[PDB]
Length: 141
Length: 141
Length: 146
Length: 146
Ligand code: HEM
Ligand code: HEM
Ligand code: HEM
Ligand code: HEM
Image (cartoon, rainbow over all chains, first blue to last red):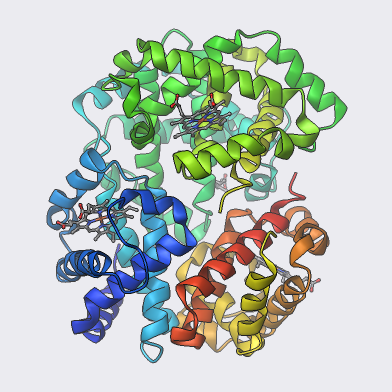
């Protein structure tokens, strides 16, 4: 599970993100679309060009969900329950794609927060995102 | 999570295994070693030839653990806690290998219980083994 | 890919002992039941709402036959699976947007279905040969991804 | 593998903007910290008991340099990564018993470390080119597995 130190690192990192959450979520999405083009079909209405408005708006929704999760490290299944239904039952998202987006978010954080993205913090953030993804894929059944 | 039907299928399947648990665990291990030779180094003292005694004995240990788990579908993290420590902290087993052994156990069951290994039962057993593997890999941290 | 001549004989020998249409219909059907997100690609197939519906679905069975007929042709070209599946790689990537991880999962279903039908004849050595085949088919299907 | 000439230039251009020894030491160190089961292969390396110990470990840093020097040579042979990594594929399979999934994980660390060092210069397009490179290196390292 997430250790005390993990929780400390996740809190510290998300404090450093602060108001830039939506920017970083948008960039994570752009990186995913570029590296892994199969993912684009989940968002058929999107202009996925650099800096597009719908990407920025959706990046903000993802960022908001992750910020709430970071304040809920001890009850993630409860906090992410509604989103788990949406992604499994409605969107039917392939579980591989959560790993892809998680990797792209880590790339994004490393690119933006070099002083803060230490190996220890990276390890904690990888666990955080994997824990979130686990809940989001928990309900195929 | 495991549905009521999943629990019914897992109970039914493990009833059908009964006294053959150790045979099937041994075979699952043999299949893993043959298909995925990288796994053999986890058991350097083993004669891994078909029907060897140490393989049969270890197959029995694995079978016993899975039988206990099948009677604990609602408290797997508690039931498999001691084994999770052993596999992560001591054995440091690569998480890929749990997927490999799970696949080989399913191959083994399909080969032995053709009347019973329906698509629905297969889906339930895949979830069961994935749930067990999740607990066994939960504690790298 | 690299199977010895003997390994190829093991594979093709056992292939002549099963009914391909059954292997294909059952492997695809198990894929849809065991990994339900894969159903995202088969909205045109109608009712996939349970294992019973999936296994009773005529379109699933028919598609299973096309999949397995392409697999069977692959078995005749084990030294060039890349060439053999190039056009299908393009189809799955450019038109269908299937993540290549799923090729591995369907290969695993083919392996399990072969064991289901062949029983003890699907030995650990036979399984190893078939894993090499499905690994090679998956690699070949992923090759033209961009 | 298949990168256009322009994509190769993007990759090699950015490679000349980093210090390879740092990329290698940090990618390996992050591998060991983020995925602790990988430490199973490095018992001879001494203290790997925390991220601080890992990053302060001289043997990790030295090994990181050998890994990255082999990566750098791969960058000069992008049209033949299979040949370039054949001997190392044999080493990792036959002598070291490393599951090939871990090649993908180390590749991912190299990608993250490149972003960490290059910042905004590691664009989504640059990342895509590098993912193709590390995917190809992983495929090449897995090729001689048996
Ligand atoms: C960290 C992991 C993820 C988080 C926190 C997350 C969060 C969210 C949230 C909060 C929404 C609601 C959007 C709204 O109400 O407007 C949403 C929708 C959606 N998500 Fe995710 N998601 C994640 C991973 C993924 C992945 C990997 C994919 C596919 C590659 C995906 C595909 C979608 C799609 C297609 C929608 C609907 C978008 C729309 O209709 O505007 N999600 N996600
Ligand atoms: C369904 C998943 C698994 C179960 C239920 C399981 C169960 C067990 C049990 C109960 C033991 C204790 C043996 C004893 O006390 O004699 C054990 C030991 C061990 N396990 Fe696992 N295991 C699983 C997966 C794996 C995998 C995938 C690997 C490696 C590929 C592995 C490697 C080992 C090793 C090396 C030992 C020590 C064997 C010995 O010293 O005799 N296990 N396992
Ligand atoms: C062993 C792996 C696979 C093989 C050999 C294979 C082969 C084929 C073949 C032969 C076709 C027919 C193309 C045509 O008739 O023109 C096809 C179509 C298709 N495949 Fe696959 N495929 C494989 C894996 C997958 C996977 C894993 C998925 C999705 C999870 C998938 C999704 C589809 C879909 C949606 C179609 C179009 C079906 C239709 O509209 O009738 N395939 N594939
Ligand atoms: C990009 C992927 C990789 C590359 C390019 C690479 C390259 C190398 C090289 C050049 C050597 C030195 C061989 C020699 O000096 O004769 C080596 C050795 C080694 N590699 Fe890797 N490797 C990779 C991935 C991995 C992974 C993922 C692991 C384990 C998780 C691993 C474990 C080892 C070990 C244990 C040694 C022996 C180290 C020693 O005893 O000094 N390698 N590798």
